[PDB]
Image 1 (cartoon, rainbow, N blue to C red):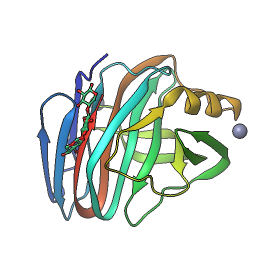
Image 2: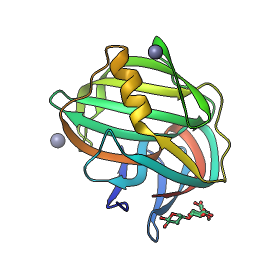
Image 3: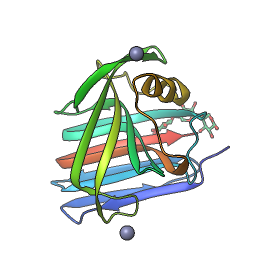
Amino acid sequence: ASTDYWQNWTDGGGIVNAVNGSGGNYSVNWSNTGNFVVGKGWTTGSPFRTINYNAGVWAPNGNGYLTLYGWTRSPLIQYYVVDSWGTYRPTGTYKGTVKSDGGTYDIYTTTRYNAPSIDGDRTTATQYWSVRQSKRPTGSNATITFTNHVNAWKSHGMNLGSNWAYQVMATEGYQSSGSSNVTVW
Ligand SMILES: O[C@@H]1[C@@H](O)[C@H](O[C@@H]2CO[C@@H](O[C@@H]3CO[C@@H](O)[C@H](O)[C@H]3O)[C@H](O)[C@H]2O)OC[C@H]1O
Ligand SMILES: [Zn+2]
Ligand SMILES: [Zn+2]
């Protein structure tokens, strides 16, 4: 299934120039931001989906994540599969690792108060992370075999909700500037 969902949220800090391009393509050029999340993917996430992307530009100047980004409800859980970042590698409570798609990821949990909610309001968010141990090379076609992460998480006691909200390959930033250009499929 092709992408059907455009994610474009900013807390209003700084400049977030996001372009919804053709197909699965988007770009972001940002300057001195607060928090923002831009990406393309699917309105209804799946634990069985293989997300493909090609980040032709990954140029954060400060904190930016090049990451799968999604939510589940019942219960409310936010998840990430971070392939690359800028000046900050996100971490949390260490749970283990998972190998997937030619990389090794550390698995983390975190609980964030006053976090952006599914719709951009605020909420207490339980978050599951796979974070690559080194930044993934960009500019070639890349796969995130998400089932590998879901299964690894499950095996470490990290169960997702039964109701799936959106699931995107995102640029998230905080307190930074940068450029990204990503095609998702
Ligand atoms: O950032 C941009 C890159 O993402 C872009 O790379 C191309 C991305 O698309 C790849 O082809 C896809 C194959 O799957 C189909 O379903 C999609 O519709 C196609 O887009 C292609 O092989 C990559 O080269 O290059 C330009 C960059 O700006
Ligand atoms: Zn394990
Ligand atoms: Zn709301």
